[PDB]
Image (cartoon, rainbow, N blue to C red; front, side, top):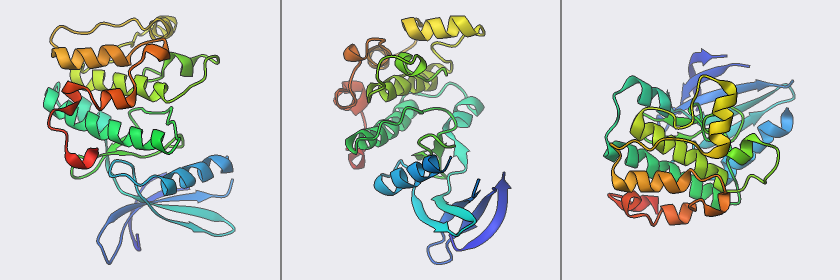
Length: 238
């Protein structure tokens, strides 16, 4: 927060830490040159305070630059998936509970994310998921998000969460194809395989999330009442 340590990449992004609390932080230095989307990020991040949504500690502004002071989470959930073996159901469920809790909180404050993806689901040093963006950082997009028509309600995040769960459990994307037209057709028709190695609870939950007609798609609140979902659910997540 207070004093800078290192430049993490490219305005630029720096690593820093609060000299009182010791908290690790990222400084996103944005130089004035669209603006409404940055403001949307800042506004959303100030409104939503949840253990699995990245914290915004401060926004420092001048005539030339905007500096967002954001809690540091140094890894992506997807590099964790890729770099390790096919993860245990217990491990996947742990992450999934955290994601769903955070999404529920978003929907509660009338925010539909629409952009739940690899780059957006960060992991901190205690392996806690942190939703980090809201839009300003294909296989994960609901059919109605892909096409123009059909309004994209809370249900598009349910679909995305169903893909995320599928990936964690199966170490593959349900709708992926090397061919562009085949991929888009698979998503729009909801064509995929539920592997036989999946527990009945995991498969039953995924099946109800990946439904084309959003009306028949399971809701966030129904998910949170699912038997498989509830196993070892930490009280703080309710």
